[PDB]
Image (cartoon, rainbow over all chains, first blue to last red; front, side, top):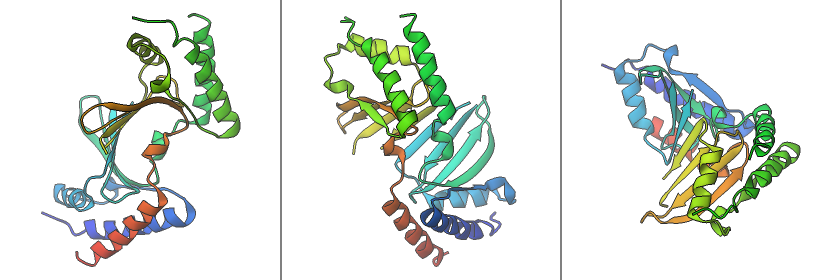
Length: 119
Length: 119
């Protein structure tokens, strides 16, 4: 039912939280790195619990849910039909994917300026 | 019923975007405080569109939605009764509210270390 791989997973998460706090460096754990059972991932999800912040990223669709441990985010990527393709744990103040990149923000401003000329 | 008074807001947004890029400083446009009609706000929300990131935060609940323009976010907080307490645009790389504070992450680390001893 369970592989026992889920607990070294918790120690890794704790180490990543330490790293985040000391360096500000975020990290990700690819859950497909280990052969986890529906049981392992199921147990890990239950241990981590649910937080107060839920994010949807539209590509397919991803969900980035803060667990009950602030700074620990459960990430599920799904295809356009809803099938899960990959799952990760990200240790971060906010997942990097949520942030608007600088080049995109500059291009946003340009788009807006152009749009203003047609209104 | 539209008054035409939301159109200047596109220029304001474009200026805030320039400011964010040049200075790294986020800005806000307090929509609730402006003399806009409901029609004006619907027009603006429709014009800015929906983007790649949607966030839900659960005191009452907030929605932090990226618009079609990267760096431009539409924020709404409702109290437990559903009443909007604030609605605003946030020009930022990520809204401040989604980030887990350092003190909360430090407590998470302590909690996880303690929990591991029980497994």
